[PDB]
Image (cartoon, coloured by chain):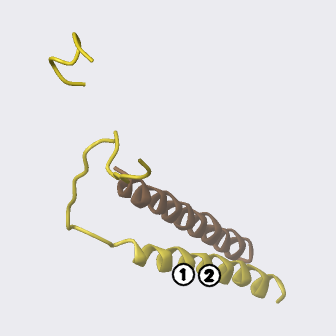
Chain colours: A yellow, B brown
Amino acid sequence: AAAAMTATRMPSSGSSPSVPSSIIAEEKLLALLAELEALSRQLAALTQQVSELREQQQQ
Amino acid sequence: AEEKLLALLAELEALSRQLAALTQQVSELREQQQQQ
């Protein structure tokens, strides 16, 4: 009634960026698709000359 | 610094296949010189 009455008396907000580091970029990209063919070409050339041992030993 | 490993890994495997081609192919000389 008196004394104190003179003054006065959720779910999901879904953030995303959190506490990780900063990020950067560059545009000098992508030789790498050539080596996948270099590697599998030269791999064949190994077997090709293993065959050239065998095809001369068989003579 | 991630993509720089993705190069280096393909680089070391290219060196391995190239050294395999060398160290295999020299054995044709070792046969042909024995055959002569």
- Amino acid type of the residue tagged 1 in the rendering: Arg
Marking on residue A53: none
In the rendered view, tell whether residue A9 sits above or below residue A31. above
Same chain under badges 1 and 2? The reply is: yes
| Percent coordinates x, y for residue B16 in the rendering | 55, 61
Q: Chain of mark 2?
A: A
Q: Residues within 10 Å of mark 1 (few under 14, many from 20)?
A: few
Q: Residue furthest top?
A: A3
Q: Which residue carries the number 1 mark?
A: A41
- Which residue appears farthest toward the right when viewing the image? A58
- What residue do we see at 63% from left, 75% from top? A46
- Which residue is pictured at 22% across the width and 53% down the height? A24
Task: Name the foreground residue: A43 vs A53.
Answer: A43
Quadrant in the picture for residue B35 = bottom right
Q: Is residue A9 above or below residue A13?
A: above
Q: Position of residue A33 (x, y in %)?
A: 41, 77
Q: Residue furthest left?
A: A6
Helix, strand or loop status at disc 2: helix
Where is mark 2, residue-wise?
A44
Q: In the picture, which quadrant includes the C terminus of chain B?
A: bottom right
Q: Position of residue B5 (x, y in %)?
A: 42, 53
> On the image, which quarter does residue A55 sit in?
bottom right
* Viewer-closest of A7 and B11: A7
Q: Residues within 10 Å of mark 2 (few under 14, many from 20)?
A: some
In this rendered view, identify the residue nearer to me: B24 or B6.
B6
Which chain is mark 1 on? A
Q: Secondary structure at mark 1?
A: helix
Q: Is residue B9 left or right of residue A25?
A: right
Q: Position of residue A17 (x, y in %)?
A: 31, 49
Give the Cα separation between the discs numbered 1 and 2: 5 Å
Q: Amino acid at mark 2?
A: Ala
- The answer to whether the residues at label 1 and label 2 have Cβ atoms under 8 Å apart is yes
